[PDB]
Every structure is written in C-alpha cells, then in structure tokens.
Amino acid sequence: SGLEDKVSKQLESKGIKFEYEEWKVPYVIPASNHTYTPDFLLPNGIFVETKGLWESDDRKKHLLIREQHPELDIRIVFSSSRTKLYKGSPTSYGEFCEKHGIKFADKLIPAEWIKEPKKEVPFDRLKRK
Amino acid sequence: SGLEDKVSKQLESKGIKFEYEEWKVPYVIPASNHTYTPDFLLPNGIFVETKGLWESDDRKKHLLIREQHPELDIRIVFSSSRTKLYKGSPTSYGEFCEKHGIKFADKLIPAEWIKEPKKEVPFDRLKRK
Ligand SMILES: [Mn+2]
Ligand SMILES: [Mn+2]
Ligand SMILES: [Mn+2]
Ligand SMILES: [Mn+2]
Image (tube, rainbow over all chains, first blue to last red; front, side, top):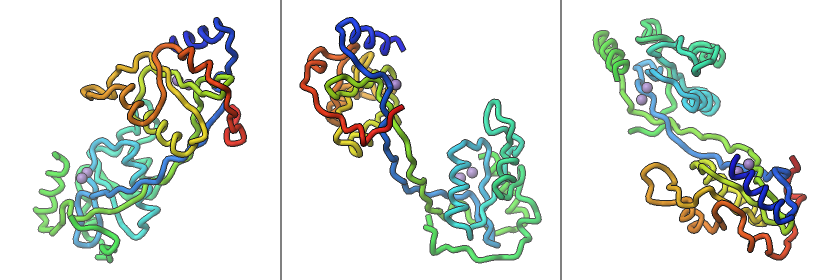
C-alpha cells in the first residue's frame, strides 16, 4: 500500500534491515453465546422462521442450532427460496437448505406441515420471552 | 414484516393457534482459529503493523493478540491516528490505542523505536510464512 511502501523505503534509506510479513502469530477467537428467536411456533411443535434476505451468518446460525439442538424442528418459509446466496453465487437458499436437511417452502406455511402429528419440544432447553 | 403478516393471516384464517417470538433458542458460535501476520519485524524485536483504515474486527484482533501473546511487542504506524473508530464516533484510532496500551505513531516508524535495545523474539511461539 502507499503506507507500506513509504515505511519500507524509510527503513532502507536509513539502512535498517527488517523482515516483511515473515512471521504469523496464532490466536483464537473465543466461543460466544447467543440466542435465536424463531418467528412462529406451531401447535404441533414445528418452529417456522419467515425469511426475506438470508445472510451468511444467519445460515451458519441454523446449522449450529441443528448440531446443538438436534431435537428442534426449525423450518423456513422464504419470500423466495430461489434467491442466490450472493451476487454471483450458483447456489440458492433452497439448494442450501436441501444440502443441509433444512425443511423449507416459499411464501406461506405448507398445509402439510400444519397437519403433521404433534411432537415434544424441549422447552426446558429454551428460554421464554 | 410483509411476509410475517401474510403467514400470520394464513394461520389465523385456519384457526391455528401459534406463538409469535415466544421462545428463544440458545446457541454457541464456536471458537475459531486464526493467524495474524504483522507487516514488519525490526532487528530489535519490535513488530510494526502499518495501518490505513482500521476496522472493528481488526481492533478486536489486536486486543486478542495482546491477551494471548503478551510476550510480543506489536505496535502500529497509522496513515492517521486521528481517524475516528467509525462514522460518528468521538474516539480516534490513537485514543483507542492509548486506552489499551498499544504503542502507535503516524506515517513512519519513530526513529526512537528503531533505536530501542534488542529484545529476543520467541520464534518458537510463532509460525514462519
Ligand atoms: Mn424474527
Ligand atoms: Mn424471520
Ligand atoms: Mn499486512
Ligand atoms: Mn498493515
């Protein structure tokens, strides 16, 4: 960058030796705690997240919850599941869900989901509003 | 939102009793491993990072490195230490550095830093590029 060049030129002009980008320093970013509030909870225990724009951190969040709370049934209703992950991506929101086992639909909750037999929700692992 | 409105109306028309944002699901964003490569290493053991724009994640990284590698001497040379942390912030890069004990300078490496007595760098704690 202009600054790196100026600093390098200065050190050389004064005859100071130096190593440039020669050493890496390892570090760990600590794990962090968060909470996610799905939009709707149906009587049969299915949670439904309505979603327009679906950002990367949001997608990672769903994968984390699936690994951390396998018993939760969290599905997504998209304004459009055909939307691509980003400006030039080949993958759609829907394809991402298919790849990771996330049940999804577009615009409205499918009649079939509402009809699914009730199942237990581990509310003990959850926090009420 | 529009989608939330349409889904809730669909559920209400079918007489489905739902809970809206009534439950919070706790989750953890996993610790992550990284490496940081300072721009310059001077003969006396001082590492210097040249920096123009200095974003929030970059500032956080520097604090993590100071906590996890207290044996290293990492300083920063800014294009301008007067720059505010972000649009609207009353705090400058320099003030942030002062608060956290980070030595800094503007435009070039201080001749006085170059003159400081050599101190051994624990290379066994680092990884060569
Ligand atoms: Mn919501
Ligand atoms: Mn939503
Ligand atoms: Mn660099
Ligand atoms: Mn730099």
